[PDB]
Amino acid sequence: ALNRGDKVRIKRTESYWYGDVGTVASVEKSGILYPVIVRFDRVNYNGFSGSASGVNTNNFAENELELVQ
Amino acid sequence: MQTYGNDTVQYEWWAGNARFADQSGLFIAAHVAQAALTAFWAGAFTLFEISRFDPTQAMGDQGLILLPHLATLGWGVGDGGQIVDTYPYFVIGSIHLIASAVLGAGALFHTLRAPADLSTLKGQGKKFHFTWENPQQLGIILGHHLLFLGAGALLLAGKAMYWGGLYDATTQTVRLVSQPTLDPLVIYGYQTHFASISSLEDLVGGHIFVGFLLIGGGIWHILVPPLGWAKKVLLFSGEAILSYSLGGIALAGFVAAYFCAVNTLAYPPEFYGPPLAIKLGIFPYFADTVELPMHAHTSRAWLANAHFFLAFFFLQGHLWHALRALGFDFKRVEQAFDSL
Amino acid sequence: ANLTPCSENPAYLAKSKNFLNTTNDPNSGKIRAERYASALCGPEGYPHLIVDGRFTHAGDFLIPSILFLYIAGWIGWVGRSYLIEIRESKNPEMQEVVINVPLAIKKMLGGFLWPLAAVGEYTSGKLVMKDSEIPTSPR
Amino acid sequence: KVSVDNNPVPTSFEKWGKPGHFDRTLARGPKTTTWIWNLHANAHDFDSQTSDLEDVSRKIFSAHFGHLAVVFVWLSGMYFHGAKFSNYEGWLADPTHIKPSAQVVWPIVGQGILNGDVGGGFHGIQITSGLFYLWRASGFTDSYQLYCTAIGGLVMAALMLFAGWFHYHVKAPKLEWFQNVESMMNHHLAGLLGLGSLGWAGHQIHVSMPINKLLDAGVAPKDIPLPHEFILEPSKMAELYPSFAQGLTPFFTLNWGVYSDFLTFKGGLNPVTGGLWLSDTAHHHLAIAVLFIIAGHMYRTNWGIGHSMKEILEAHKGPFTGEGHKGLYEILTTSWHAQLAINLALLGSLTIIVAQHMYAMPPYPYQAIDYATQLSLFTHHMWIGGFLIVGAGAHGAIFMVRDYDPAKNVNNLLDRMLRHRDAIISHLNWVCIFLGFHSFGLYIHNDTMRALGRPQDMFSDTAIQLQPIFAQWVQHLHTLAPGATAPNALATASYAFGGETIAVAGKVAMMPITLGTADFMVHHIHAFTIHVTALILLKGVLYARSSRLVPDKANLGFRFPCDGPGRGGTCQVSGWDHVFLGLFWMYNSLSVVIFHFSWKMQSDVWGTVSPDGSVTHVTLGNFAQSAITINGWLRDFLWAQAANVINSYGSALSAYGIMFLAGHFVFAFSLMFLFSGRGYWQELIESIVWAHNKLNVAPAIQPRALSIIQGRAVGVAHYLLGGIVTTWAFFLARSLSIG
Amino acid sequence: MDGLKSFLSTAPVMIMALLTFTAGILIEFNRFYPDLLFH
Ligand code: CLA
Ligand code: CLA
Ligand code: CLA
Ligand code: CLA
Ligand SMILES: CC1=C(/C=C/C(C)=C/C=C/C(C)=C/C=C/C=C(C)/C=C/C=C(C)/C=C/C2=C(C)CCCC2(C)C)C(C)(C)CCC1
Ligand SMILES: CC1=C(/C=C/C(C)=C/C=C/C(C)=C\C=C\C=C(C)\C=C\C=C(C)\C=C\C2=C(C)CCCC2(C)C)C(C)(C)CCC1
Ligand SMILES: CC1=C(C/C=C(\C)CCC[C@H](C)CCC[C@H](C)CCCC(C)C)C(=O)c2ccccc2C1=O
Ligand code: SF4
């Protein structure tokens, strides 16, 4: 139950962004497990060694997100 | 300011003094704060020079800058160029210190209590309101400053004649100079050897002549408004009058730097050190004939070189502001390099 | 203390007659020899430093100590608040790679109010972040 | 045949404020701090930015002009420091006694003690580069000629910078101008090497010969005629040599035998000044000029005559070699990395040849007397040569990964050599292990025989002696050469093979170097380490395409850390990591080579001389029976000769002590990057990001640890820097203490 | 020169100008007042 562009804190407890805020880019349709597309500004450890950047967008669930707006 | 369009202009903090150049009260406040800073430097540094003075040595070798400026007027000078009693230097230093205190108090008064523009006043404050476009009020301010400089020249004249005695390099005593020169033809002829005059009566005669000339210019500028022949040739803005004043003070600094290094009676050789030699290396500086041990220089060298370099950079400040007053963009010179 | 002062130490008085000139001033070793006379030396002739906190030797330690504690705090505050004012302009990455040098010069000049600003930021809560909104690592 | 495009790239300063524009993944944005290291790791990778063979080639050409500006401003700094802040005219007044110094230090923090008394009242730091003897060989007299040479060098530095801007942004050449490789080869042969050798032959005839002749006669400074006065008055040149009255006319009628009084074949050394004869080197440079310009017309460009190299490579094919060199002309004119590997290999071996020739035939006046100049010039050129050979092993692998197209070269020498990579490497490491046991286990064996108190079972000369008979026979042939196999030569090629002891100013220039069994063992040590470095680099070249462990190595790139922890583990498998290992092995090889040089030359060659003919050396002949032990290499060389670095405080050689300890520091600092891996430091840096996020000071540039290749690169860089700085400080402080 | 002001304000040139200014004032303070172990 989130909009498209609201700040939300993550409570994944196993991700790189754990406690960092993110903007919900889109919420997909129901039925799937992790529909909440969340984008961040800080990239994670991703890619091969010596890569210039990583990824920021990620599919998250609903019950592990704390809305801060 | 110039304001080549964009009437509501915003300056950043590194040009932060350009923000109050249109307003009136802060324009008074910053300048009287600056005059408070000059009076503070004068009084506090002649006190600091009394604090670091040794009578067992000569004067100009130890960096004595303000005490020779007071001893040329002959306040606490004894015999043979020796200073044994320094009361009036401390007196004039305390006078300048309390004068700086009251000038800074007036500066903070005009910053805080007096408003920005003097057009919102009702009584005498509305008469002091000025704008950079009407030249009449600027002429009134111009004439009153002319009158005050003439009054200062008359006070120096009274110090030379009645209020005390000056100092000479011939007898090396005080001298109550009376009966100066009265002829203006020889003053017209003094445009060639003004550096070495070698007579104090001619000095006080030139001072009373330039003082009466200043009073004449003052009453002339108060009496008549500025005419229309100069308004077609002189620009009327803040930076224009800033440019004219900057060129004037740069020329005055060059003249004072020439006067310091070569004179002998307005700068005595026992107070400022020996007269200098104009030596051009990369830039024309002023070198001494003898060399001081601890890489040191006399007061004449410091005064002449500092006033020369400050006059040079004030000439380039006049150049910057005068090209700014003529409509030049100054990112046009960056756009000329970028088009290339 | 068991250390003799340099005003009467025999090894220091034997070693001060030939102190080497460091700078181009030819009397630099002699003025160093009379500058280090106030300090105390051991049995070798070298000036030791009492660091216990007693103020009679505070010129050995405490007087430069707080001097550095100004300048480091100055650098720290200039490095901190500048990051805050590039937390958003349009993109902080290029403003960290190339420097917004008028903003940097503004912070570099204004950094001499750093300890009062530090107590102000500590009281306003904008110095120390909360223990829950910080991106911690998983246990 | 000139093909130039006009204005390909606009000159603009706006691209300078956007770092990382040359690569596609760097110009997006610095999201992570590793982008910064990538900005320096791909700044010269011009093959990864452009992929059209025309933009990269003009980028290389302008980069050559920029580097040439760097060398010209460096050479200008050498001549300017020799002009203004040196004692070149003072050293020229008295070359034997006082010592050269071309750097004065500002006394600020007590470093005025570095300005030691080098002789004649002048203070400063004594130079060991020895370009003063270069200047006396060229013919410099006063400091004004060095000053005008520095001014002309700075003029040509700005001229090369303007040529770089002109050849990239105004008039840049096309790809066919670069691929004219036969015109490039014969122009570089004749017009660059041969024409430059003819220019220096003319300078050695007119300037270097008469000035050094009257300086060997004993003419004081401010009494030598100016170098142009010999041309302006040929009588002053004709009174020194009788053949100059004959004029140019015997040269054209092939009457060269009357030129024999000033183009001699003396050889050996000059007994007055302790260097090569200037008439010998003048005749030498003239002969090299003639042979190079003759060889500078071999390749056809426009006039039909000449060898195009394509059918040269077509014609060489044998039974073992299949199709021969069919395809290599298309390889070496379409890939810059193969040309870089060949040129770095041959420039590295050239620089090592330069070091191995500039110690037994000292070409400069008073160079062999100054031991610090001789030792520093030897070891520095040894290190530059070994570095460039490792770069050959690098760019061979880069050619294999990104510039090797297997469809064009089928059954040629490159394909056949890649087809039996196991039969090459499995014999190369066998001879590595055989040399390793038979050059190091000999050292362990007589170390143990000396430690067990039985010296009759060692490998000494009094013990079981391994006499190097082949080089001793070669020395016998070089001693017997002048008069039998070189009849117009008076002296030998050098006095290191065999002959008299050359003494100049109380010191020894060059005496014959006998080769005992210690030289046998240390030469096999040298051949062993050369074989191992030529194993790591060669198996980085051959195994860069694919393998049996990982057969997908070409698609992963040249510079990748690993394939993963699988197959037991595949870390350090790329062609880059073989260069990373070969750099340490070049360090070990050249350290032992310059150690053998320094100890043998200061135990059997150098030292003072006595008027009755007896020679006393610096270490009194330790290399005979004490260079065969590891404890002998430690006690008598690394402990005894390091005392001049240790006990030199409060003196002129005081900076070398705090460079000795500095080099030990950078070695020990390199071990942190070499031993540890990235993921520890990533797990620690993220905790420091937590401690920054607690105070809201965490940077928006994401701070994270170095890459794995970056960690190995900074480890090998600090290792080689620390070891070379330690050896530099030790060699300079020792050989400046011994004179 | 709209790009020269950005190139002179990159991180290496600004940190080199700041370290040159810091080393300059440190060397000048150590020339006019040398050998200060304490206060
Ligand atoms: C009569 C004196 C006078 C006055 C009233 C002004 C007034 C003004 N000038 Mg200015 N100027 C002057 C002299 C003067 N100038 C001289 C002599 C020069 C030549 C060096 C300049 C060069 C100059 C430039 C290049 C610019 C101005 C600008 C300006 C305007 C913005 C306010 C400002 O200066 O920024 C506030 C002042 C500061 C922040 C000070 C800067 C800090 C300096 C670098 C440190 C001081 C240097 C040094 C330590 C001084 C001590 C010397 C020695 C004892 C060691 C303002 C109207 C600016 C303008 O028109 O833009 C709107 C502008 O770009 N001026
Ligand atoms: C100016 C920004 C800044 C600030 C405020 C801090 C503040 C802090 N750092 Mg730190 N750090 C910085 C930059 C900064 N760091 C940088 C750039 C690096 C990479 C070299 C580090 C590496 C680092 C490590 C490895 C550690 C800290 C730690 C700490 C904390 C303890 C104090 C300390 O040891 O600092 C001392 C600072 C250093 C040793 C390195 C900084 C040295 C540079 C020269 C300071 C200036 C940086 C920058 C150029 C200035 C920007 C000015 C701006 C106008 C552009 C403290 C919160 C420690 C910690 O976790 O505490 C719990 C710790 O272990 N820092
Ligand atoms: C003719 C000489 C020459 C030329 C043109 C090249 C050219 C090239 N090499 Mg290369 N190389 C050479 C010699 C040469 N090399 C030699 C002799 C070696 C053996 C050491 C190597 C080893 C080598 C490796 C291992 C790699 C390259 C790579 C590359 C390519 C990219 C360069 C790059 O990103 O570095 C940009 C420049 C730098 C990173 C600067 C390096 C700074 C060094 C490490 C420190 C210098 C220490 C200094 C002297 C001491 C003082 C510093 C301090 C104490 C004050 C480029 C085509 C890379 C490549 O192709 O990857 C795909 C690559 O990975 N080269
Ligand atoms: C001092 C430490 C050390 C030693 C001894 C070696 C030794 C060796 N390295 Mg090596 N290496 C080292 C450090 C060392 N490395 C480091 C730091 C690096 C980092 C860059 C490398 C990188 C490296 C590479 C990249 C390669 C080697 C290779 C080799 C082998 C070459 C063959 C040889 O010399 O014959 C064998 C010589 C010895 C074993 C030393 C002699 C010792 C005596 C004679 C043997 C003991 C006698 C007897 C067995 C004792 C019996 C007692 C009983 C109780 C067992 C050799 C085993 C190469 C290899 O293995 O292929 C050929 C190879 O390719 N090394
Ligand atoms: C910046 C600014 C400004 C300005 C200001 C100013 C610049 C000020 C100045 C001021 C001043 C500058 C003041 C002064 C003061 C003074 C004082 C403070 C004094 C005191 C002294 C004393 C008290 C002394 C005493 C004594 C005596 C009398 C004698 C005996 C001894 C003794 C020495 C003790 C303004 C606001 C506009 C605006 C904003 C910014
Ligand atoms: C006096 C003395 C002493 C003592 C000392 C002590 C004992 C110390 C302690 C210490 C401690 C017990 C400390 C604590 C601390 C804690 C904390 C908690 C801290 C805080 C910090 C922070 C928070 C930071 C911040 C900042 C600043 C301030 C600036 C810059 C920026 C930053 C952010 C970095 C001694 C004996 C040595 C000697 C004598 C003298
Ligand atoms: C310490 C370490 C790190 C951490 C490396 C870091 C944090 C790099 C440190 C760089 C700092 C910022 C120093 C800057 C480097 C130079 C001193 C810059 C020169 C600046 C002057 C000219 C002013 C690794 O990432 C690593 C990776 C793989 C194997 C081993 C290691 C490893 O040992
Ligand atoms: S240890 Fe490192 S380099 Fe080796 S396989 Fe694992 S990840 Fe790759």
Image (cartoon, rainbow, N blue to C red):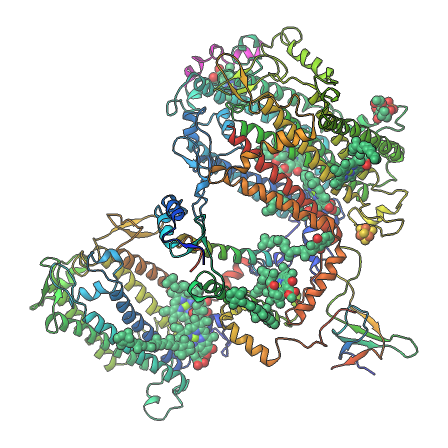
Figure label count: 0
Query: In the image shown, does D454 or B275 lie closer to the viewer?
Result: D454
The furthest residue to the bottom: B122
- Name which residue lies at 61% across and 41% down: D67
Q: Position of residue D63 (x, y in %)?
A: 64, 44
Query: In the image shown, does C34 or B38 lie closer to the viewer?
Result: C34
Query: In the image shown, does D699 or D430 lie closer to the viewer?
Result: D430
Residue D739, compared with residue B188, is above or below; it is: above
Q: Position of residue B201 (x, y in %)?
A: 10, 64
Taking the image as shown, residue D564 lies to the left or right of residue C2, namely right
- Name which residue lies at 80% across and 25% down: D312
Q: Position of residue D83 (x, y in %)?
A: 44, 35
Q: Position of residue B141 (x, y in %)?
A: 29, 79
* Magenta-colored stretch includes residue D133: no
Residue C17, compared with residue D145, is above or below; it is: below
The furthest residue to the front: C2
Q: Which of the 4 quarters of the picture holds residue E6?
A: bottom right
- Name which residue lies at 51% across and 22% down: D365
Query: In the image shown, does C22 or A39 lie closer to the viewer?
Result: C22
The furthest residue to the left: B179
The furthest residue to the right: A31
Residue D620, compared with residue D176, is above or below; it is: above
Q: Which of the 4 quarters of the picture holds residue C94?
A: bottom right
* Magenta-colored stretch includes residue D247: yes
* Magenta part of the chain: D233-255
Q: Which of the 4 quarters of the picture holds residue D12?
A: bottom right
Instruction: Tell me, yes or no, if residue D223 can be seen here.
Output: yes
Taking the image as shown, residue D351 lies to the left or right of residue D251, namely right
